[PDB]
């Protein structure tokens, strides 16, 4: 194909060049984006230019100090990073200007025109919290005992603190999630969040540690405070082996970074004021690889067991995964489940899905029993093997 | 015309037509968006759906948008339908005339709808080939490829390797229109050309029908 | 190296807990104790049709009256069998009686944990064994099956299965078998769990079965007699 | 601690082979070169001493080539230090085999036995393998005239002309180019030996002090191993001038 | 050649007519535009106030306000008044503010990220499809796994439950893992963002979890999408310091990937395609399914496969019809894609020395004996090993 | 970060006499006075400024300081040493008598049903500090939810001792 | 090169000790061709577009490509680090491996490569 | 056997780092195929690396452990040459073989050697100074029953009986190439087994019958190592044949 590719290459080159000129040239051709409904707004807009209260500058109130002599003094930080002290809003409530609250202040006079919705005080904490979906119990395999404890510990005290008073304890400040990975813990966690009507805020430990340590300290404190404002919440710290790893500090390693972030979290757990009915949920491989220092067991409460599916245990997950899916089968859920070795739940879930991909290969559009049989044999080998480091010599 | 590519193009076109005037445009676009009718068209419908749900205020616009979502359809296990007879690619317009007239005149009338109803044409998802004296009713696997390495081929057969598509499995237009029956190693040639034609296919078989193949 | 004295705060070795995962990739072994014998089943691991079942075994003789079927890591099984074989033959000259199925299992169990990163000798190790062995033989107390594991514990069992899933293969065996039953039903019960836990399914060169009755010597089954046990799965 | 280091001596590395064995070959490269060449009626060893100094007294006239036995000879390519130990092991093995055998020690037999000790250390004992490749020349009846090459890796090789020590790749080809299979006689071979040594050295200029030349020539009823005095080598250094022309022509 | 040429000549000429016709429209031809739009522009520019100071429109409040961050350095809480509507403004875009007193005049312009510009490389493989044959079975799989759930919804909808979320392309180089990612991406025309794994470990610390989350998040915004992570072996292999090697660096990057792909934060029908030449470095949790789905393994080329692998390399060069393929299969076999590339390069290299400016069978043969030896030599031979 | 310490203490000096509660002291009490290639370089300076503020300049003997550690294997020796922090108060791990005393408070708080057979409950517990006493009472209450009932009993309180002791530990072995 | 077959130069290794005037010949051809000879001595000193390697592939390539052709003369002296000599045997050699493999494969630039 | 660290530490993979590293060390002893006939059991090795200044004896992967048991080695990889590390397994194997001849004087069994070797590798784990092994051997030899034996052992410690097995350059791959070539005729015909060994070696090596040296061993006669020159004559016909099965 050497001679054939040159011809095609030249013909595109010429057509492509000509395009550059046409696109640039046409443009939007001196049109107005607003169209007809904004014309009335232009006249307003002009009045505003004359006005001194427009434009407002967004700022935030950093600190409350009283030496009052007009109307209450607040120090705000302007975004040109000059500190200015302003005074109580022109007509709005003093109960709307608070510490860590956003405020709109005039650009030309610098007094609070109107307060604005709160929080923009950290840059980093705002970044660290991410999107929230909901997946339900149907989608997450098993109705097992391991599944049942997650609900009872998280859902019940937050939903009704009444139950937890009756027993004569406080709703957990802390809650511990443990179990090896590839079991659908995050999936289960999403599922209880919808039922409880308790907002879950996902957090990543890898963002928290950074090159210079201190950013992660201010971030963690600010993060507790935000959650504290929210009522019946969960701060779910996923994939942490920073706030999640071993207790030890080398003193020239990245281990320094871990230790500052953990240390503030201990202060937060107790609180400046206690945290009755506020849950922080933490995921670890097992509680023995978690700090005996960050774990100060009264506060953390119940440790919720999740464990690697059993042969019986995987028979159960597989019915849920299969049933949820649309599949035409003749072979049964138990056979294939026994077929799998003890490894992870994750191989056995992939069988249900892989049988659907074999159907497209097979030139069907939905699965059949033969696709199912094919999927167990390839899947058990593939995922388990061809992975993991080939050393556990000379590490700390 | 069937110009190149259909994977990217109706999605892209729905976005640009928002700038251009008239709700009728959107209705006319949906015609292109047919092709393999559950392949391209599910996406095309959803995207126009958003903008149509977005704003409405006159019965007239709502009527146009309604024509655009449903017209696009023919879906879930239903075969390839696009304006084309399969065999023609030299063919002259006379099947075009009923929709063509309707594009030219006002579609702001409900009246336009009589001519617009018919755009009757078929391509098939069948690959039922008729042997030399076998006259076989079983289907035949094929290989599809979007592009060519040669103009030795321009009667629309590409190599038998490529990506395979099955027997009684969606036949798809540009960027996957070209079709060879994969069976060059079995030395079978179509007498009647393969594209997923409307015509009943025919082969001269020097080895009969090949089964299914995984890939 | 990285710690090989490693205790968890609960009070067991991490290294021992790691040892099981190796067994799981390896071969599958079923031992069932019957009143009328001990039957031993083991995976041959076919992968060509050229590997001869009569010429090679993985049911091996501890004594002429005692058998052991191996599972998990193959290299590891061989070291335990060679020390156990001599102990057994030396026992026979001295006492003039066959060695109890328990007596041989206790000796091998000593080797399982004795490891440490440094100060190692042959009696010690640099990492604990990940094999579980099913020592089955007939003695004067009757037919016994004793089970030895990677934790280096010996337990009497009238049915144990260990393989691809140790606990899995034992749960299938818990459903079928009953304590006191005929030889054919015990031999059937061993094959049946075996194919379901494995990726591989039951054949007559896929698995190896040899049966020890009391009042008989250890017999490794002939080509034909191996095929007879296949008809009842 | 000792548990937080690496040196991968007995432990295999990601390579599939130990660091210590591979490193020994690098040390051999920048140390004086030893070659053995085949002749029709003898075999010879020619070596570059580890002394680059301009003044030697000749206290020991074996500082590279040591004659073990009256039936054998060796060279050292590498560090003189690991050689010292090896030289003492060789005077015993070479004579022990002879007490029993009553036949000139086979060149092959000697090297395989020695190579076994070189590998023993790297595999076990927690000792590094000797930094010396020893070039053995000898004669036995059932192979004929021989040259065998010894490594720290426990690799042996049956050769007719080979060189180990500094710039070995060049050196073996250069011995092949001038000297084919069974071509050159003992006297003309001694010249060839010096010619390659002049070209390949750690530090230039070939002199009597820098070279030691040894002959195995079978005399009347005995196989005679002699290390040539400085005086004789000098006659070969002029012969080596003549030899440069001769290779080309 | 001649068959193609009449159509080629006509296409270039059709395009010429298209260019020339634009000029007449902007200069002379008007009917809705006229003198009238010219005046609309003047009138709007003077009210609007030139210079317009750029802002970025984060979000719109429906009461006649918007929250703008001015790009100068200090942010302003503006009104949405003057030539724009709330709906006309779009999030994550650049907007025009009146310079004298800031109210948001409007969105003409869109804002592209700084990140995305560097990452991005254009979609299209330099080896055309059905000429990356050789492991031809394998090439098909990626089209099914990444390309298909986006291209065709029909099978997925009937199949039910979650779709795929990646593929992992692994095994020895030269089996064309990069060419495959580019094909599917080309076809769909999903924005193809490309980062080498070595960017994940650079001198600064925590750049790895940072880059990967931003890259994905940007893929979700510009969705549907294909993220290509090229050659993730570097994580362990590289270090600029002690902190850049070692466990903290390796974990943080792996941990980020796990949350991002299927975890809480999830991703849409956005796929990640990973190229790796070693899954020794990679964990069992990123080789776990349902955040990788089907894994594609390429094995060493087989004797018959090797002839098809050799053809691809030959097609990029000049097309052979005089190379004996058997000699290549006989000399070496169960050696990589990379070995077939090594035979080809060496032939080209000898021809270059003469100033022969072609390769022929002769150049392949002469170079072929040295290359096989050379393969063994690449790994240490020491002194004599 | 270091300047902030200096300013923060200065704030205490004005206000004087005052008590500055410092929660934890491995971040202005790192052990290290030599390090490289880490965030520990900035952490060491905040720690060094702290040592200086305690040193005598008067009105800063008026102001008091509470510092806390749960460790000793990362405590800074100067701050432990007197003349930075005069007093060294030790809190030991609860005695047999004390362990019973704390543990009694917790059972009391809960709905009355672990106040029967209290001698038995007091004895069986081992290596319980204060945290572990709170930990058992909440885990006991958890077991009452498992049952599905509002009645608590002494037996659950007993299962908790085994279940949590600041570890997974379920008190089990792999033998037979 | 299109005629010769082999992809236009990706990696050309000039190796061996200096003092033989190896740099000097490179300068000669680079001047004549009118490619800018941009010397790296082993340093990410002369990466100022972010100032750390591994992004010294992408930014450096785009600038070079824009004002093309360019001959990027990377001199790998490798006297940097003591923990960059355990990352590849040079801080620069880590950069060069990134750049080499990526650039070979990138866009059409393998047998259309002209930024050597 | 003296060190001051453990030789290996366990993983939750259930692999031994040192045995896998050893498998690459034994592919240093290049590719070896052996097929079992009716009366001649034959193995052949890759590379003699001839330059006619060398001896052929010194590079051998064919080692005589006894005069009625012989073996050729490899396993998996593609890594560099070196006879030597493999040679060391031979030196242990040859004592092991010889000690059995003292015990049982009839032609010693294949089974004994393979079993001793699996256990030998586990044992080396236990000692901190001892370097483990992980190799495959193509054990060839005869019993006192006079019947042919070809046995093979693996790094996994497991030995199996076979009619044809190949090791080297992908153990499963050379083995599978033989599975195709195998027919029922092959093993009884004396002539046919030889051609199988030469087609497998001819794949990975250029110009064999100089890099193909094979030995036949017999029921009544000891090890015979054939000259290379008579092997080349076969290679020329056989390479014609090799393309045919493909």
Image (cartoon, helix red, strand yellow):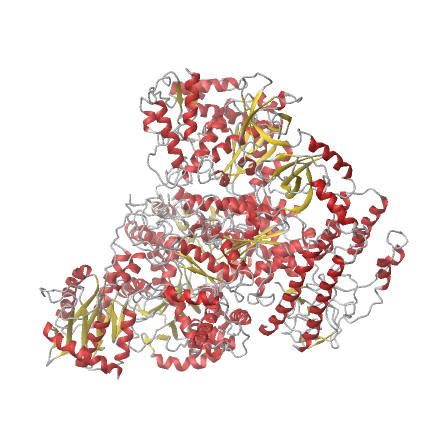
Q: Residue at x 49, y 28 (%)?
A: A268
> Is residue A54 toward the left or the right of residue D224 in the image?
right
Q: Nearer the viewer, residue E207 or C91?
A: E207
Q: Residue D172 location in percent, x, y? A: 28, 73
Q: Which quarter of the figure has residue F39?
A: top left
Residue at far right of view: B111
Q: Relative to residue D154, is residue G92 depicted above or below?
A: above
Residue at far bottom of view: D249
Q: Residue E188 location in percent, x, y? A: 65, 57
> Is residue B102 toward the left or the right of residue E308 in the image?
right
In the rendered picture of this protein, how many numbered marks are placed on residues? Answer: 0
Asked if residue A371 can be seen in this view, the reply is: no
Q: Relative to residue A94, is residue B181 depicted above or below?
A: below
> Is residue H119 toward the left or the right of residue D226 in the image?
right
Q: Nearer the viewer, residue F47 or G69?
A: G69
Q: Residue A147 location in percent, x, y? A: 57, 37
Q: Relative to residue B209, is residue D153 depicted above or below?
A: above
> Is residue A27 toward the left or the right of residue H24 in the image?
right
Asked if residue B72 can be seen in this view, the reply is: yes
Q: Relative to residue H21, is residue D229 depicted above or below?
A: below
Q: Quadrant of the N terminus of chain A?
A: bottom right
Q: Residue H215 location in percent, x, y? A: 35, 75
Q: Quadrant of the C terminus of chain A?
A: top left
């Amino acid at each position: 194909q050497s001679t054939y590719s040159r011809q095609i290459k030249q013909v595109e080159d010429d057509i492509q060049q000509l395009l550059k000129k046409i696109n640039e040239l046409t443009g939007i051709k001196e049109s107005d984006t607003g169209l007809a409904p904004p014309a009335l707004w232009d006249l307003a807009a002009d009045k505003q230019t004359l006005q001194s209260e427009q434009p407002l500058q967004v700022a935030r109130c950093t600190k409350i100090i009283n030496a009052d002599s007009e109307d209450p003094k607040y120090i705000i930080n302007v975004k040109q990073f000059a500190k200015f002290v302003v005074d109580l809003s022109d007509q709005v409530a003093p109960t709307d200007i608070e510490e860590g609250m956003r405020v709109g202040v005039d650009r030309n006079k610098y007094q609070i025109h109107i307060p604005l919705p709160p929080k923009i005080d950290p840059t980093v904490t705002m970044m660290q919290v991410e999107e929230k979906p909901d997946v339900t119990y149907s989608d997450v395999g098993g109705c097992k005992e391991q599944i049942e404890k997650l609900r009872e510990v998280v859902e019940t005290p937050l939903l009704h603190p009444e139950r937890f008073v009756n027993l004569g304890i406080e709703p957990p400040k802390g809650v511990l999630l443990f179990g090896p990975p590839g079991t659908g813990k995050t999936l289960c966690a999403r599922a209880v969040a919808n039922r409880t009507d308790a907002c879950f805020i996902p957090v990543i430990g890898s963002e928290l540690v950074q090159k210079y340590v201190g950013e992660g300290a201010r971030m963690v404190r600010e993060l507790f405070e935000m959650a504290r404002t929210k009522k019946a919440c969960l701060i779910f710290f996923d994939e942490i082996d920073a706030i999640g790893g071993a207790r030890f500090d080398d003193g020239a390693g990245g281990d320094n970074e871990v230790q500052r972030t953990m240390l503030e979290l201990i202060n937060q757990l107790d609180g400046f004021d206690p945290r009755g009915n506020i849950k922080v949920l933490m995921a670890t491989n097992r509680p023995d690889t978690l700090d005996p220092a960050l774990m100060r067991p009264g506060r953390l409460d119940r440790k919720i067991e999740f464990s690697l599916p059993d042969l019986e245990g995987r028979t159960h997950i597989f019915k849920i995964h299969a049933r949820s899916m649309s599949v035409e089968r003749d072979i049964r859920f138990e056979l294939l489940a026994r077929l799998c070795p003890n490894s992870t739940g994750a191989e056995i879930r992939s069988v249900c899905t892989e049988a659907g991909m074999f159907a497209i290969r097979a030139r069907r559009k939905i699965a059949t029993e033969k696709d199912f049989l094919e999927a167990v044999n390839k899947v058990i080998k593939s995922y388990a093997k061809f992975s993991a480091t080939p050393r556990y010599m000379t590490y700390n | 015309g069937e110009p190149t590519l259909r994977r990217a193009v109706p999605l892209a076109l729905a976005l640009i037509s928002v700038s251009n005037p008239r709700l009728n445009i959107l209705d006319t676009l949906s015609k292109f968006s047919h092709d393999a009718d559950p392949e391209v068209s599910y996406n095309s419908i959803f995207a126009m759906g958003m903008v149509g749900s977005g704003t409405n205020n006159a019965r007239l616009a709502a009527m146009l948008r309604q024509l655009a979502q449903y017209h696009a359809k023919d879906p879930n296990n239903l075969f390839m339908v696009r304006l084309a007879q399969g065999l023609t690619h030299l063919g002259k317009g006379t099947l075009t005339l009923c929709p063509y007239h309707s594009d030219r005149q006002l579609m702001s009338q409900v009246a336009v709808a009589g001519l617009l109803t018919v755009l009757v044409s078929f391509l098939d998802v069948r690959n039922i080939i008729l042997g030399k004296s076998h006259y076989v009713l079983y289907g035949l696997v094929a290989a599809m490829q979007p592009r060519m390495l040669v103009t030795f081929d321009e009667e629309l057969r590409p190599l038998p390797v490529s990506v395979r598509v099955g027997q009684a499995v969606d036949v798809v237009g540009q960027a996957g229109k070209p079709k060879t029956i994969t069976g060059f190693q079995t030395h079978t040639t179509p007498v009647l050309l393969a594209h997923g034609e409307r015509a009943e296919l025919a082969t001269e078989e020097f080895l009969p029908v090949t089964p299914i193949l995984e890939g | 190296d990285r710690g090989v004295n490693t205790f968890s705060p609960e009070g067991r070795l991490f290294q021992v807990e790691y040892a099981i995962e190796g067994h799981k990739l390896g071969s599958t072994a079923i031992g069932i104790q019957t009143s009328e014998g001990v039957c031993l089943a083991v995976e041959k691991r076919i992968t060509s049709p050229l590997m001869e079942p009569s010429s090679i075994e993985k049911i091996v003789e501890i004594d002429a009256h005692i058998g052991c079927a191996m599972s998990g890591l193959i290299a590891d099984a061989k070291t335990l069998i060679d020390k156990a074989r001599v102990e057994t033959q030396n026992h026979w000259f001295t006492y003039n009686e066959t060695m109890t199925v328990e007596s041989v299992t206790q000796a091998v169990s000593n080797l399982a944990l004795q490891f440490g990163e440094e100060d190692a000798d042959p009696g010690a190790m640099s990492r604990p064994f990940g094999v579980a062995l099913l020592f089955g033989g007939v003695d004067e107390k009757g037919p016994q099956l004793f089970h030895m594991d990677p934790s280096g514990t010996f337990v009497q069992c009238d049915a144990r299965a260990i393989g691809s899933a140790s606990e899995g293969a034992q749960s299938s065996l818990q459903e079928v078998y009953h304590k006191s039953t005929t030889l054919k039903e015990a031999i059937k019960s061993s094959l049946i769990i075996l194919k379901q836990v494995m990726e591989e399914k039951l054949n007559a060169t896929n698995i190896e079965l040899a049966t020890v009755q009391p009042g008989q010597n250890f017999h490794m089954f002939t080509k034909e007699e191996l095929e007879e046990v296949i008809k009842d799965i | 601690m000792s548990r937080r280091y690496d040196s991968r001596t007995t432990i295999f590395s990601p390579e599939g082979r130990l660091y210590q064995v591979e490193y020994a070959m690098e040390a051999i490269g920048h140390a004086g070169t030893c070659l053995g060449i085949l002749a029709n009626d003898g075999v010879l060893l020619a070596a570059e001493r580890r002394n680059i100094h301009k003044l030697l007294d000749e206290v020991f006239f074996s500082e590279k080539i040591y004659k073990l036995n009256e039936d054998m000879a060796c060279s050292v390519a590498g560090i003189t230090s690991d050689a010292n130990v090896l030289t003492n092991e060789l005077r015993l093995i070479a004579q022990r085999y002879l007490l029993q055998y009553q036949e000139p020690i086979p060149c092959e037999q000697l090297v395989t036995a020695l190579c076994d000790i070189k590998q023993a250390y790297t595999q076990f004992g927690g000792k590094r393998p000797f930094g010396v490749s020893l070039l053995y020349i000898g004669w036995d009846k059932h192979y004929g005239f021989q040259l065998y090459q010894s490594d720290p890796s426990g690799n042996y090789g049956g050769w007719k002309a080979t060189c180990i020590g500094n710039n070995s790749a060049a050196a073996v080809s250069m011995l092949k180019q001038d000297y084919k299979e069974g071509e050159m006689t003992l006297k003309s071979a001694l010249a060839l030996a010096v010619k390659v040594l002049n070209k390949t050295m750690d530090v230039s200029k070939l002199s009597a002090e820098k070279v030691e030349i040894a002959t195995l020539t079978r005399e009347n009823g005995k196989t005679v191993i002699r290390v040539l005095k400085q005086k004789e080598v000098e006659q070969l250094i002029k012969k080596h001038e003549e030899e440069e022309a001769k290779a080309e022509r | 050649t001649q068959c193609r040429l009449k159509l080629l000549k006509l296409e270039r000429i059709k395009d010429y007519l298209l260019m020339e016709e634009e000029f007449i429209r902007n200069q002379e031809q008007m009917k809705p535009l006229e003198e009238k739009q010219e005046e609309e522009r003047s009138k709007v520019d003077d009210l609007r106030g030139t210079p317009m100071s750029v802002g970025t429109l984060e979000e719109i409040i429906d009461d006649n306000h918007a929250i703008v961050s001015t790009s100068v350095g200090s942010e302003h809480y503006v009104s949405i008044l003057s030539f724009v509507d709330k709906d006309l403004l779009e999030p994550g875009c650049s907007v025009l503010l009146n310079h004298k007193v800031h109210a948001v005049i409007g969105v003409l312009m869109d804002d592209t990220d700084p990140l995305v510009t560097v990452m991005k490389v254009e979609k299209a493989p330099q080896e055309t499809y059905a000429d990356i044959g050789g492991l031809d079975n394998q090439i098909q799989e990626i089209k099914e796994s990444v390309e298909l759930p986006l291209t065709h919804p029909e099978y997925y909808e009937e199949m039910g439950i979650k779709p795929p979320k990646g593929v992992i392309l692994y095994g020895p180089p030269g089996t064309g893992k990069t060419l495959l990612a580019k094909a599917v991406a080309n076809q769909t025309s999903a924005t193809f963002l490309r980062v080498v794994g070595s960017e994940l470990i650079q001198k600064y610390l925590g750049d790895g979890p940072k880059l990967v989350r931003e890259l994905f998040r940007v893929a979700e915004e510009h969705a549907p999408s294909i993220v290509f992570i090229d050659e993730i072996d570097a994580i362990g292999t590289k270090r600029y310091d002690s902190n850049s090697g070692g466990e903290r660096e390796i974990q943080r990057t792996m941990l980020e990937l796990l949350n991002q792909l299927d975890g809480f934060d999830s991703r849409g029908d956005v796929k990640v395609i990973m190229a790796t030449n070693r899954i020794e470095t990679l964990d069992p949790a990123l080789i776990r399914p349902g955040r990788i789905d089907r894994k594609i393994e390429f094995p060493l080329p087989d004797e018959k496969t090797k002839k098809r692998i050799f053809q691809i390399h030959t097609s990029r060069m000049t097309l052979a019809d005089d190379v004996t393929l058997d000699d290549l299969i006989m000399a070496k076999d169960d050696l990589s894609g990379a070995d077939i590339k090594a035979i080809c390069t060496e032939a080209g290299l000898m021809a270059l020395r003469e100033r022969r400016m072609k390769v022929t069978n002769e150049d392949f043969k002469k170079s072929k004996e040295n290359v096989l030896y050379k393969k063994q030599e690449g790994t240490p031979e020491g002194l004599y090993l | 970060g270091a300047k902030l310490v200096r300013d923060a203490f200065a704030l205490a000096k004005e206000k004087a006499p005052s008590i500055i509660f410092i929660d934890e002291l491995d971040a202005i009490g790192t052990k290290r006075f030599d390090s490289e290639k880490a965030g520990d370089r900035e952490v060491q300076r905040t720690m060094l400024e702290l040592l200086n503020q305690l040193d005598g300049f008067q009105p800063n003997t008026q102001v008091k300081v509470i510092a806390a550690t749960n460790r000793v294997d990362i405590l800074d020796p100067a701050l432990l040493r007197s003349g930075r922090l005069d007093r060294k108060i030790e809190f030991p791990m609860p005695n047999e008598e004390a362990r019973a005393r704390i543990m009694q408070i917790h059972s009391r708080k809960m709905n009355v049903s672990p106040d029967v057979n209290y001698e038995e409950l007091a004895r069986c517990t081992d290596d319980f500090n204060g945290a572990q006493c709170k930990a058992v009472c909440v885990e006991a209450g958890m077991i009452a939810l498992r049952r599905g009932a509002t009645e608590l009993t002494h037996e659950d309180y007993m299962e908790g001792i085994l279940e949590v002791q600041a570890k997974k530990k379920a008190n089990l072995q792999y033998y037979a | 090169f299109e005629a010769l077959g082999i992809a236009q130069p990706k990696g050309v290794l000039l190796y061996g000790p200096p003092g033989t005037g190896k740099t000097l010949l490179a300068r000669a051809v680079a001047h004549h061709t009118d490619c800018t000879f941009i010397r790296v001595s082993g340093s990410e000193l002369v990466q100022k577009f972010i100032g750390e390697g591994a992004r010294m592939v992408r930014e450096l390539f785009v600038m070079a490509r824009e004002h093309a052709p360019s001959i990027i003369f990377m001199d790998e002296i490798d006297s940097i680090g003591s923990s960059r000599l355990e990352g590849g045997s040079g801080g620069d050699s880590e950069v060069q491996r990134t750049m080499l493999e990526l650039l070979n494969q990138l866009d059409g630039f393998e047998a259309t490569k002209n930024i050597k | 056997m003296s060190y001051d660290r453990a030789i290996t530490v366990f993983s939750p993979d259930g692999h031994l780092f040192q045995v896998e590293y050893a498998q690459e060390a034994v592919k240093k002893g290049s590719t070896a195929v052996g097929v079992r006939g009716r009366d001649i059991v034959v193995l052949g090795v890759e590379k003699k690396s001839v330059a006619k200044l060398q001896d052929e004896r010194t590079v051998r992967k064919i080692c005589a452990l006894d005069d009625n048991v012989c073996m050729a080695f490899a396993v998996v990889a593609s890594v560099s040459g070196l006879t030597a590390d493999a040679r060391i397994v031979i030196n242990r194997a040859r004592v092991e073989c010889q000690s059995h001849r003292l015990t049982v004087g009839d032609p010693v069994t294949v089974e004994y050697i393979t079993r001793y070797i699996a256990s030998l590798k586990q044992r080396y784990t236990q000692s901190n100074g001892r370097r483990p092994f992980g190799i495959s051997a193509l054990i060839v030899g005869f019993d006192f029953d006079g019947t042919p034996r070809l046995y093979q052992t693996d790094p996994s410690g497991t030995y199996h009986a076979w009619k044809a097995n190949a090791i080297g350059r992908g153990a499963k791959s050379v083995r599978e190439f033989l599975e195709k070539n195998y027919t029922d005729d092959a093993i009884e015909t004396d002539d046919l087994t030889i051609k199988l060994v030469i087609k497998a070696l001819l794949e990975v090596v250029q110009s064999g019958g100089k890099n193909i040296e094979l030995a036949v061993m017999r029921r009544d006669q000891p090890l015979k190592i054939l000259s290379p020159e008579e092997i080349e004559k076969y290679v020329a016909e056989i390479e014609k044949e090799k393309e045919e099965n493909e």
